[PDB]
Length: 322
Image (cartoon, rainbow, N blue to C red; front, side, top):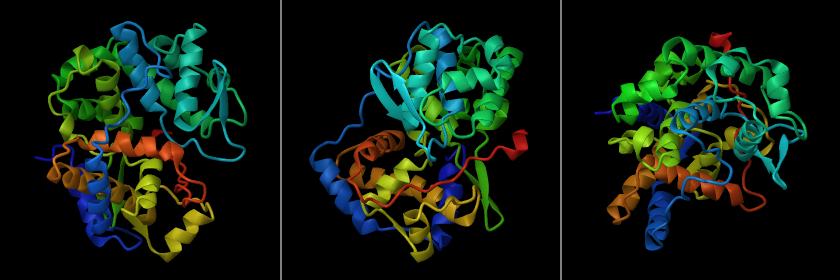
């Protein structure tokens, strides 16, 4: 009963993967250590996430996760907000919070549909520039116009139609919002990931404390989010191993083309690294959903020692949405 096909399609990749493999001995050791001290993932962060009424909050979560990709590049994109400097995901979250607090209607489908390059450039203004600035402007325009066209400008209408099924909501989102379609091929077979769509559903659960629009009966059916920080943490913990050419490529910070065998192997092995860690923890009496193991690992990613292998650098592509 794998209704999105993420676990099934990524499993075919892991079985034939040339450049990446899971160290199942490292999985058992990490599980033993994590189970011994009952590791919980950080609660959904209240400080850097915007909050308001249920209609605006639901739309805020859709917007946040629509543009939640690819924050790396030199010079480093950094954001000043409320007396602190942010980079990566937190720069994204802080930027949207800053904008909404200064009265920028980023929860209004009518504003989103029309948002210009200069609007998003201002919202994301700081040191350097957010990567793929134009891409994020196009995605936000797509997001607004699908909200206005299909959901009466309310993402709450899409959530109500899911009937408290996380899996049904991911499917509703990828069906209606083309930029959420996150699939690839490996040796001629489709591989399904749905990173941003699964983050979105888990973010609703967090933001709404598992109630109202954040109520879901099947959160265990979500997989890990095949991003670039979680594989970096899994490599650091010895769970993911990289073959010679891929290891050197990451060490030199050489970019890996989206949808290339190396990238799809990292992503597939991310999903199964987390799933194998989930199973090993459960076996030792520490039961977490795969998305919770992902949150836990993502949190470790924000304080990795100096000298850990760098995260893989893949520019997200939306060629089919141009």
